[PDB]
Amino acid sequence: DSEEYHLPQHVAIIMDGNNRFAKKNVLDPIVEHCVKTGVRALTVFAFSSENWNRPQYEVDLLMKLLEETIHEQIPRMKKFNIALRFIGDRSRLPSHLVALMEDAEQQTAHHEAMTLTIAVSYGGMWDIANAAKQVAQAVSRGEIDADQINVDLFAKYVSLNDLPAVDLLIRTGGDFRISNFLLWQAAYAELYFTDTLWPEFTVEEFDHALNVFSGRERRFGKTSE
Amino acid sequence: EYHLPQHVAIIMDGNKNVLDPIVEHCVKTGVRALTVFAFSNRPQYEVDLLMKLLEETIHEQIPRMKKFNIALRFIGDRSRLPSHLVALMEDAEQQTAHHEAMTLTIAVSYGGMWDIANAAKQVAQAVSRGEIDADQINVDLFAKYVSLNDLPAVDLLIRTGGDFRISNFLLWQAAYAELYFTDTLWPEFTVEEFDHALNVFSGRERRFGKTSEQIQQEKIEKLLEH
């Protein structure tokens, strides 16, 4: 405990609003600011560019863009001691994209002050059902008694179970939905919604959100989680 | 045009009956489901008082449910509830089951994580019996074990009391819900503010679109109304 310290250990961001933007990288200064300030985990969802329910030509372009962006980010993540991680379904992804994700995770694992997780082909319901599948597979092997399955056991199989629970979730762009993102992990997260469009989102407003989180922790306490 | 939610959820938090005008507004506007959670590990005497209050409230509400053609439902863990409360819940559900205009669900000893892990337990028990291959488990199969799966997904979730958390309520069911937060404490929550929240919901659906499930629900309801 501490009277002065109220920094969230795990921040999640739903990046939205470029679809409404009429007229330099936004995420990079946020990521750098987080690791410099001591945030332990940052988990992000590109609300438009990870929506792969589009014509196959567009999905192909989006995957190529993701690959080029991962490649460009690896040396930057090494420079700032950030571990890159990916969550989501990999079973239907092109082999080159899977290899590139593994490569990026392997190149950035050493000497990591913060984990940056990118949601790729991810959904919160998918995550929960995947955890249930893994639990049932363990039951089939005799490793779990199905009658003893409870919240604490199930939590060990959901994505990001080795990181702190999400303390703060930010969504830009104006909508007030968490849109099937980190449903289990953000069960007790403070939710910060802003109409600022993602391309116009600033480190200053991010700091404001952190101060809002601190004030809400003072006002409503920390939760059970 | 004007967009009404199919399923409203409320976290009643506060740091005359408040819920009754809200229930009546839902019935009058065609809301199909209203699910409520009294937000707040206490001395046993306080737990007993709360249980007795819940029992008396269920008793008081049954005739209103008949009057407005509302079906009563309860979600949450029943394994540690007093047997008299469990029997009263079963009786209320059976007495109101034929009512088909709206479902009012009261969450008692409920948590969203509990709900999800309970679904996982049921699926794994079926696997243990050899009824299901664990490799078949996916979203569509799992969804049938989560509470309220026969009702529309939550479109609008209201939380009173000032905090901006969903606090482990309907995590699966509110995956695409619009979230409406108000500083108003629950005892002071009015049907006028509920009307305002519904108006805000309509504007947000116009600006940010309907969910996919909402669009399919509306297609189906148009096909059926004919």
Image: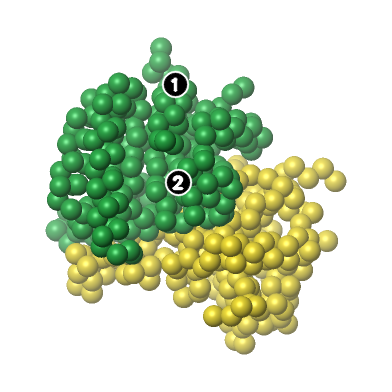
Chain colours: A yellow, B green
Q: In the rendered structure, which amino acid carries the disc numbered 1?
A: Lys
Q: Which residue is mark 2?
A: B12
* Vertical comparison of B207 with A40: above or below: above
> Residue A144: x and y, percent?
23, 71
In the figure, residue A64 lies in which quadrant? bottom right
Compared across the picture, whether A117 is left or right of B41 comes to: right
User: Which one is closest to the eye, mark 2 or mark 1?
Assistant: 2
**Residue most toward the bottom?**
A111
Labels 2 and 1 positioned on one and the same chain: yes
Nearer the observer, A138 or B164: B164
| Marked residue nearer the N-terminal end (2 or 1) | 2
Label 1, residues with CA under 10 Å away: few <14, some 14-19, many ≥20? few
The answer to whether residue A126 is visible is no
Amino acid residing under circle 2: Met
Task: Say whether residue A181 is left or right of residue B57.
Answer: right
User: Residue B155: image x %, image y %?
Assistant: 49, 38
Q: CA distance from mark 2 to mark 1?
A: 21 Å
Residue A29 x/y as whole percent: 77, 68
At x 74%, y 50%, the residue is A196
Between residue A57 and residue A146, name the one nearer to us: A146
Judged from the image, the secondary structure of the residue bearing numbered disc 2 is strand
Question: Which chain is disc 1 placed on?
Answer: B
In the drawing, what numbered circle is on residue B28?
1
